[PDB]
Length: 64
Image (cartoon, rainbow, N blue to C red; front, top):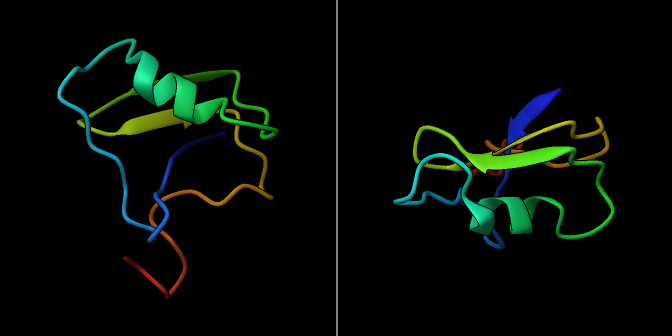
């Protein structure tokens, strides 16, 4: 399953380097989550392999 990562306040994380963006990848595998691959796609840290128990963007009714 693929999804987008959020931020502390819930906002997303856009980047200026598309493609293998270590920044997004590092923030993807951050800790226990199951992110097999995490790169920036469409100006944003995108990840693939997030369990349903993982919070992704956008957020619930409580958007940023």
